[PDB]
Amino acid sequence: KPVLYYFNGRGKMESIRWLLAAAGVEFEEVFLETREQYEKLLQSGILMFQQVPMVEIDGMKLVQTRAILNYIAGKYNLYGKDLKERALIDMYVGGTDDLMGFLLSFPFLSAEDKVKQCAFVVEKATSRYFPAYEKVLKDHGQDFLVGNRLSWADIHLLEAILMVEEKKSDALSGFPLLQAFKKRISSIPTIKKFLAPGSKRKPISDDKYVETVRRVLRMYYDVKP
Amino acid sequence: KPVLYYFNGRGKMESIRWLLAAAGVEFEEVFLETREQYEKLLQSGILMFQQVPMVEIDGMKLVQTRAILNYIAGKYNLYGKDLKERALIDMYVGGTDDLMGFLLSFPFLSAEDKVKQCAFVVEKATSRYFPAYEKVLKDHGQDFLVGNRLSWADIHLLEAILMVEEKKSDALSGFPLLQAFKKRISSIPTIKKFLAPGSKRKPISDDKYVETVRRVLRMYYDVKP
Ligand SMILES: N[C@@H](CCC(=O)N[C@@H](CSc1ccc([N+](=O)[O-])cc1[N+](=O)[O-])C(=O)NCC(=O)O)C(=O)O
Ligand SMILES: N[C@@H](CCC(=O)N[C@@H](CSc1ccc([N+](=O)[O-])cc1[N+](=O)[O-])C(=O)NCC(=O)O)C(=O)O
C-alpha cells in the first residue's frame, strides 16, 4: 500500500490523492507536523531533494509531484494507449497543472493579495483554460478528453474545475460541454466515492495548514501573489 | 520536420532543442520578433493555451514544455524501458527542471536581483541538486543515471550543469562523479555536435532577448527572485 508523505492539507499532494482514489487504490498518509519530524526525514535521506510530496510506492521513494502522478497514471491505465494519446494527456494536464498552480499559494497570501489572486485565477479560467477544454470536447464530441475513455487528464481537469468553482460558483457558466463533463466524471463510482463525505479528499487549505508548513519548513513566511 | 515556435533565445525551449539534438533530430525554428506575430498566432489558434513554447511534430500542435519533452523522450527511446525507469527519469528531471527553472527568469531580473538569484541557484546546486545526483551515480557506479544507457535524465542534467557553471565555473568542485559525468555525456556524438560551434544551441539570453519577449507579449517587467 502506497504511503503519501505531505502535510495535512491539499497542496501539491491533493492531485495525487485524486488520481489514486480515481484508480480505486487504497493508500496511507503520513503528515508532517513538526520541524523535528521533518529533519528526522532529511537525516534518513528518503527525500531525494529534501522536499515533499514524497510517495513510497512499489519499492520506490518517489519525489517530484509530476513523476509521482506520471507513474500512477501509467500503472493504472489512465495514461492513454500510445505515445500520441499520452502527449495529448500531458498537454492537457500541463494546462490544469498551471491553473491549479495559481491556487497553490493562495492560503499563504494576505487577504489583500488573496482578493487579487482570486480575480486572476477565475479570469485565467474563463478566458484561457475553460475555452480550451470546452473546445477539445466540442471538436471531439466524445465523453472524455482523450481516447474516448477515462484518463488522468479527465481527473486533473475535474479537480481544477471544482477548485475554480470553490472560488466562483458560476465560473462554468457559458461552457455547456464542460458542465456535462463535470456530471459524467463526477459520477464515476470511485470519483463519486472520493467526493462523498468521509473520503480522504482534503478541504481548502487554511491558516492552521499554513502555520504548520511554516514551522516545519521555516519558509514561505512571505509568499507573494 | 518538427518546428519549434519560440523566441530567438533559450527560455523554456532550450531544453527541447537539447533533447531533439541529442536524439539526432533536425528541426526548424520560428522566432517571435513582434507583438504582431503573436497576435496573429493567437488568431490561428495553434496555441491551445495561447502560450509558447509550441512544437509542431507528427501532426500535433503541442504546447506545454514537459508534454513536448515527454513525447520526444518517448519517441526516441530516451525514456527508459518500463514504468519504474520512467519514474526515476521523471524524478531526476523534476530536480533539474526546478534547478534550471530558477535561472529561467535570470535575464529579466534587475542588476541587483541577479546577484541574489545567482547565489541562490549556486546554493541549490551545491547543497541540494548536485549532491543528489552525485549520490545516484555513486550508488550504482554506472556511467548513466538510469538503465545504464543514455536517457533524457542524463541530457537534462548535463544542460543544468553547464547553466550553473556559466554562473560559477567551480560549482562542480566536490562532485567528481558528476565531473566525470560531464565529460562522458558531452563526448556523445550528437551532443558533442550540439555543443560544437555553429549548432542551433542558444547563448546566454541578453538584454536584447528580454526586450523582445517583453514586446511580443507585453508581460514580465517586474520579475522577482
Ligand atoms: N517540483 C517539486 C517541488 C516540491 C516543493 O516545492 N515542495 C515544498 C513543499 S510544497 C509547497 C510549499 C510552499 C507552497 N506555497 O504556496 O508557498 C505550496 C506548496 N504546495 O505544495 O502547494 C517543500 O518541500 N519545500 C521545502 C524546501 O524547498 O526546502 C514537486 O513538484 O514536487
Ligand atoms: N506551463 C507552460 C508555461 C508557458 C509560459 O509561461 N509561456 C510564456 C512564455 S515563456 C517565458 C515567459 C516569461 C519568463 N520570465 O522569466 O519572465 C520565462 C519564460 N521561459 O520560457 O523561461 C508565455 O507564452 N506567456 C504569455 C502568456 O502567459 O500569456 C509551459 O511550461 O510551457
Image (spheres, coloured by chain):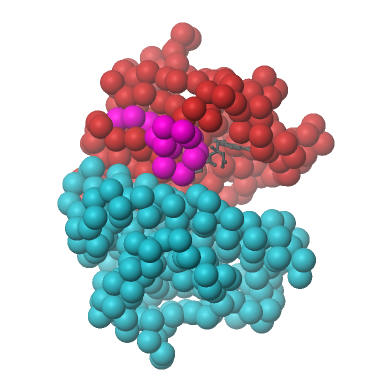
Chain colours: A red, B cyan
Q: Is residue B17 above or below residue A162?
A: below
Locate the N terminus of chain A by quadrant. top left
Above/below status of B134 relative to B11? above
* Residue B95 visible (yes or no): yes
| Residue A9 is covered by the magenta coloring | no
Instruction: Give the residues drawn in magenta, as a range.
Output: A42-57
Tell me, yes or no, if residue B7 can be seen here.
Answer: no
Left or right relative to B134: residue A179:
right
Residue A170 in the image: state x and y as whole percent: 63, 30
- Residue A154: horizontal and vertical position, in percent? 38, 36
Residue A155: quadrant of the picture: top left
Residue at the (66%, 34%) spot, across then down: A218
A47 falls in the magenta region: yes
Which part of the image, by quadrant, shows the C terminus of chain A?
Answer: top right
> Residue at 44% across / 27% down in the picture?
A5
Residue B211 x %, y %: 69, 76
- At x 70%, y 66%, the residue is B114
Q: Residue lying farthest top?
A: A198
In the drawing, does residue A149 fall left or right of residue B17? Answer: left
- Which quadrant holds residue A3? top left
Rendering coords of residue A189 (x, y %): 32, 17
From the viewer's side, name the closer residue of B123 and A3.
B123
